[PDB]
Image (tube, protein in one colour):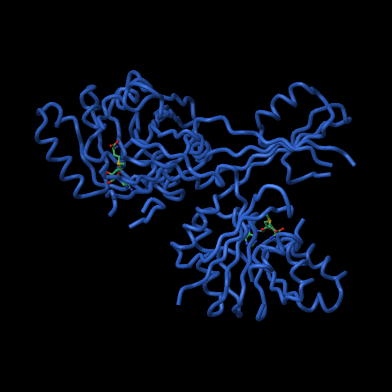
Amino acid sequence: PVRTPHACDFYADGTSEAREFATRTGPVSGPVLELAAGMGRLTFPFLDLGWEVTALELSTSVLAAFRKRLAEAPADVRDRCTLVQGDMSAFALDKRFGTVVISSGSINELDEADRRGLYASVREHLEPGGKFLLSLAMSEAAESEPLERKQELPGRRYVLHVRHLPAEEIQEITIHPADVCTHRRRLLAPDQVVRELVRSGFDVIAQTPFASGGAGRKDMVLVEAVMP
Amino acid sequence: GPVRTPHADVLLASVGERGVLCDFYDEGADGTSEAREFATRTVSGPVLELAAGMGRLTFPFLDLGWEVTALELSTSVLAAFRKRLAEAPADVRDRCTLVQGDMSAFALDKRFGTVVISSGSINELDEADRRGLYASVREHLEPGGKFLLSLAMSEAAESEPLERKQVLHVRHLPAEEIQEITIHPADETTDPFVVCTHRRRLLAPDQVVRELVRSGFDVIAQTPFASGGAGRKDMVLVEAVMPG
Ligand SMILES: C[S@@+](CC[C@H](N)C(=O)[O-])C[C@H]1O[C@@H](n2cnc3c(N)ncnc32)[C@H](O)[C@@H]1O
Ligand SMILES: C[S@@+](CC[C@H](N)C(=O)[O-])C[C@H]1O[C@@H](n2cnc3c(N)ncnc32)[C@H](O)[C@@H]1O
């Protein structure tokens, strides 16, 4: 239990986010691997686009919920979805895919070392010319231009320029009855993940901001990465 | 090779053939006050200083009478320290113990009443290596001994995080930034116009504090201070102890 300065813990439809993934993939022949699929907040929208989806999830309990939802769906929908228990930071399906997909909530679950395991696992499950697509929440600090500081320093005079670039923040939530719950989660800057992707061998061909809920301020980025 | 910053991009473009871009840390043509912050918040006996470098802090510490063990990873840096230590008075020279080691995974046949590390040093370490540091420090602290850290504090790290309510309170807390610098001569001509760039890790002081608590320390004080004695307080002095 985290006792924030404002003192119980604390522990949305995926159609728009899913359509954004579909925009940045285009033709997609063959199956799509979705990492940390949860109970299908994105997977069901993906299936509705006609995609064949291998949905990977770590939790037994979450898998049961997903399986139940799938039993409730029409046969043609359920038939296009393959559920697999695994760890997105270290998995082996002995099988490659034209497209690999991961959501922001998912990637922000992993620390730095685990993200490297993720990147490497993905490399092993991409077919040549395959696409690795990520969505990433973008905070106010992450989208803003960094304030550059300038100082004149001395014999020879130099000008020093200093900027601080966003890398990682904590999203803190205190739930509050109006007349008290708690959560802190990781919030990586899209630019930080892009740096990490390049470092792990990927070329990042595009970063498209979008609105998670499909309207209003653009609060997310869709990153397309490919293997050279 | 070197980091190509937006301001560097435009400089080099508008300078042509005279322009040279290199990282700040290669071909490249403070201390006593940060040292005093440490001295102010501390001795019964020997101090351990981690990642001592060439002794920007260590020599100030030695001038206070301290027995210092200075741990450093780089062999050439240690050689350079040793050279500076050779020109030092015999009494200063005898109170200094130089040791080669990794501050993320080190083991000495000694414990200490005080262990110190500066901002530049802890920011060299990724998250995993920082956990290795905290565990190692705990093992080298005598009962009641203190772990003292100095931590650079950016403007975003210094500000009160912006809230947005709906009631649902949402704050975004700084955890880690990248400090990016660009340095060039104030003129334009010069003969060779060299532009230095560098990118480095810059942890939020509160993030390191969260990590220390998680690691088993009690953080008993955090005092902001100015790295050049005066001006904006751009640094925090953290004191941590083991509970018991
Ligand atoms: C914030 S949710 C995102 C789920 C979904 N893609 C969405 O957009 O709603 C993170 C999910 O990843 C799962 N998860 C956490 N770590 C995992 C791991 N290492 N491998 C696979 N799944 C993981 C959790 O069980 C949880 O269901
Ligand atoms: C920013 S300087 C700090 C030096 C000194 N404490 C000061 O305030 O001037 C970083 C120093 O840490 C050393 N270093 C880097 N990683 C290290 C490690 N894992 N263990 C010990 N020293 C390390 C480098 O060789 C360098 O001397």
